[PDB]
Length: 303
Length: 303
Ligand SMILES: C[C@@H]1O[C@@H](O[C@@H]2[C@@H](O[C@H]3O[C@H](CO)[C@H](O)[C@H](O)[C@H]3O)[C@@H](O)[C@@H](CO)O[C@@H]2O)[C@@H](O)[C@H](O)[C@@H]1O
Ligand SMILES: C[C@@H]1O[C@@H](O[C@@H]2[C@@H](O[C@H]3O[C@H](CO)[C@H](O)[C@H](O)[C@H]3O)[C@@H](O)[C@@H](CO)O[C@@H]2O)[C@@H](O)[C@H](O)[C@@H]1O
Image (cartoon, rainbow over all chains, first blue to last red; front, side):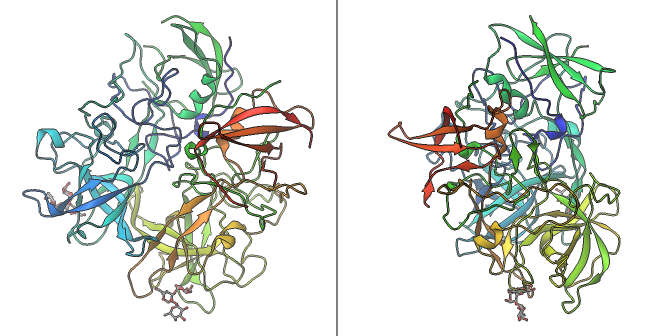
């Protein structure tokens, strides 16, 4: 059977790995030959694999709990634990972090490049909301041990001149990166170890590259206290859920990829993409591609 | 022609009129017999009608510019203007506010409830982001003149004890309501005037009511002298883009509605909704419906 794709431009699609920032370009990079991401992972048969969702914006904000302490050496990095409502009992067969939570990489061992939970605040002590939400720096684990630097687990630290209220719950809305955060450091994601069924690290077919649905992330700095040196960057994804939603009506034939026509202006320039059942859409043999264009189905091809 | 609906629960659907907040329940209220909203308006034949979009999360954040002034009477209500990237020249045939911007109502001439735009910050004077993004209160116009107090246009006011940098861009991410803003005040939307084709007011047929895809909006206060009166509330939407996205491969037949089966638990309880072409979900003849269920197509009925 044939596949019908609605003519929705990528500019009208959600960036699953970074909501609140629309898709600006389709990005091709020759130095990116893998994808160890946990957000934006979709499959034809398995649905939303890994830790992704079909509602990226809804599952974007999290909560954590203070741990009444600080990391060894650095007094400002108060330790804290991510709260998981989806996995209340700590089952080793289920993901530790809440579904849809951010997975931007920060580096192996770098006390110069920290993330930015642009909005973190304590509860109101009344159960109605939160209070004094402002920009703060965060990262996964403690940046000391091998198993807690890139671990994508529930332990984090928050940079704050004062001390967090012990045992009190806080909100988390990850928006921004600070320090020496380049685009390549955000493209990598923290390693996940354990038993739970996480998404594998995919690689493109031999000789082909990947379209990334890039977006521009602005800065959110502070001009007081110790200060926040946030920087502007870019974020990439595997594919938006909007494109792959249509494919579930008639799944791909057994061991068959699809040929997609990306048409920009009338019939002047029409690029060819090859979409696989594992989630990624490959091109061939990079440069940015405008988002004002629609995807059209050509035929079914063999890998 | 039949309509196949994917079994996606409403808890996995985006709330158009309030992203960053998952759908909590399906809400049906007897006193709500209309919807003058400009967000969440979709049509089977006309596409995204009014001021809505298929990417509510991407187009949620806005930018405004200062006007070097304040409202008469209240010194703290600095005046600004919402800049539209989709309508650079102020053509009266296009919507004044940028597409996808918030439309939460507040009440005409109200100095007791100022839904807070929450996150607002000045530009960094570097061209790469914004700085000191903090929680501030906002509203449309100046709450004095009938033509621009509650009229959903470019003029807004921001409450800030210190003056705003004149002629500089500011970021805004509206999230929260302050003062005595109940659920009913947020339900209504500011009136629309002009020549642009805005979404009309929808009234359900006699003897039927609506399903509202409601969600819970927390509070984000401030501990300072002036402070913020942020309160918790709920937000409702007419329709989610995920449901109407499917109904485009085969559009509805000539002047016929659809009968949808909402199946809960293990099929013990099945409710029957009526979906119309205007984009509203009729639920016959209010209480609260859980989101743990999937939609199923039954037949085509005549309104
Ligand atoms: C070397 C550096 O000196 C001070 O740096 C602060 C900035 O602090 C932040 O950035 C630094 C350098 O990248 C580093 O990543 C640190 O973990 C982080 O806190 C920042 O507060 C700016 C404010 O504009 O001021 C200085 O550049 C010191 O605070 C850092 O701890 C670090 O030793
Ligand atoms: C000092 C006090 O200020 C006003 O009441 C404040 C609140 O101010 C805020 O709310 C009121 C309406 O409730 C109004 O909308 C004002 O523009 C807004 O900023 C607020 O400061 C709270 C907590 O911080 O305290 C008071 O309720 C004013 O209404 C009072 O008459 C009085 O002057």
